[PDB]
Length: 337
Image (cartoon, rainbow, N blue to C red; front, side, top):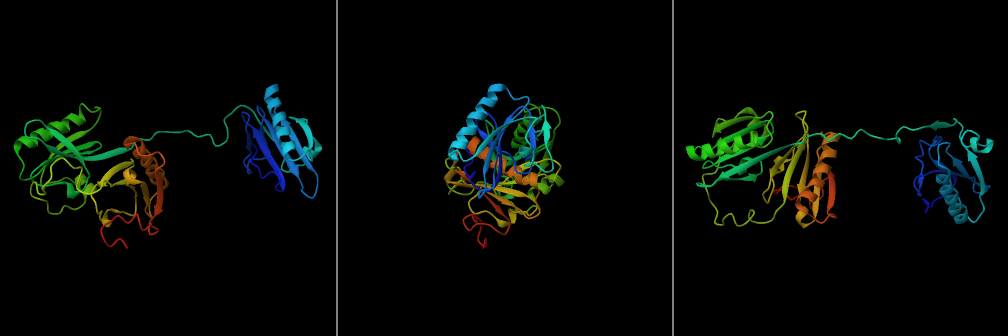
């Protein structure tokens, strides 16, 4: 029941937690929480071994009992060779004391070391929806990428505090209004507080709309290919997301949901999460000039993906720094490699 490598040379320290002897962090040794009891084992191998039972002053009697029991669990695993001593807090032994040069530090109450103030920072999810339905209206989430837009329809860009009803040139005044409504829906209905809605016309996009999508290209006419709303897309089901706090916020944006991804999507100042969780892996690409929070966050959304979509909880989350990308990972247009 012990970390096992106890025969190894030197001094070993463990804080009896519940009934489990936890190895005391090598740095932290010499500081004893008085509410607990400890097992400190000093053996100079080609010398004698000494198992010392340190008793916290604030340690309950029987919480000491358990430690005593752990002592023998140990002494036994070492064939009785060890010499055992019951060191009380504050009245230790010259030999025990000799284990700690610097000296001894006793703590009371307080929180375990490393205790942290855990704050759930908001993450703004930028979404793009494609409005459809002459009669009854229904908007479908699309990836925030110009490949998603066409001139015949209206789209809703929910970019956090700013929401846009972008309307293609060849779209109706009607679709424009449904779009306007759905957008108002979000702002208002969907948790009111502070969000400004703006109707945008094909060609006159605002600065934000470009900071997100990038310089506008030429867009696709109306409805091409011969399938219906039957298939998700055409081929597979892998999606690419971007994680960046560049705005002082932390935003997650689906930047692609197509088959061959464009390498241009991978920006060096961010982290991305290429979700292939459906058939196996969920990669995380760490761009050279990205920060820790972005890295830490990308991990968290890869987990949020496994939950949300119900992937085998034992799906592999592979991190890949930039340049050091795995060959499989290169699920991008050609030239990736």
